[PDB]
Amino acid sequence: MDRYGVLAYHSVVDDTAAKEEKQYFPQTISANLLISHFNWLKDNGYNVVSWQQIIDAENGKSTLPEKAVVLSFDDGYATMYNVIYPILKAYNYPAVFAPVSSWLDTPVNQLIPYANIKLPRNVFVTWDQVREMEQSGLVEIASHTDNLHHGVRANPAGSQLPAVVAPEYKNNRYESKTEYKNRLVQDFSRSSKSIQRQIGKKPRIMVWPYGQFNDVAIDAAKQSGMTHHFALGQKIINKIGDRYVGRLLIDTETGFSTIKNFLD
Ligand SMILES: [Cl-]
Ligand SMILES: [Zn+2]
Ligand SMILES: [Zn+2]
Ligand SMILES: [Zn+2]
Image: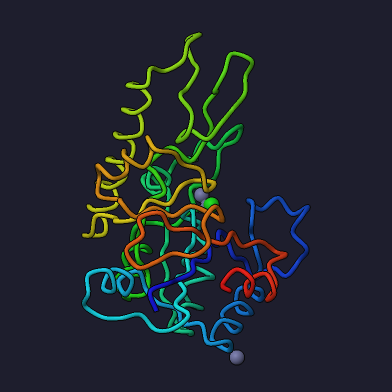
């Protein structure tokens, strides 16, 4: 066919504990739930394809199988390497991984400023780990911004919005449209270079933090080679060649009927 679905995952842990009170990051699920999805896909005729097969399809080099599905993992959590990757290898499932590049670029001796707190560097993967995963041929490296996976103050009353989608209010004023666009263009361009130099491939997908984007962000990403962009459930079916790619956001309540209705 000419259609494909996309699933969006974040962290995956061995812990089967109920998660609501455990202080993980949002949308963290259990490895059992992940396996259940991986089993349900293959036992229902869904074929996991790599991003390369998508690109090969749009370029008229090969066709996709029926009920094509892409798997995607956001943020750069060490669980990508420690929990997810062994499972991808066991299933021979490829995937797209979107680490925040300034998090990875943080030296091992430093914490990562993250809203009100500072995180141990090994919450996240190292670049050695990313190289190994990419070299397997199973994992495509996408961008998830360099350092725009945070909020900015978006008004004088102290409202905070994702940095990608809001001119910043600081020094008692709003960014100019030109300042705001510049902020996205340079961050995205540093992300592309940060990934390229470790990995050998410029990323060719932008994955938006929190699913949120706009026209300025799209054009900023496009300028650095990321015309394909991954959002969340604001679009369900993707056709070969689409720039705007929708995804299902996975959470601990995502059961088979949820996945089925989406992929239907
Ligand atoms: Cl997301
Ligand atoms: Zn099975
Ligand atoms: Zn995400
Ligand atoms: Zn994210």
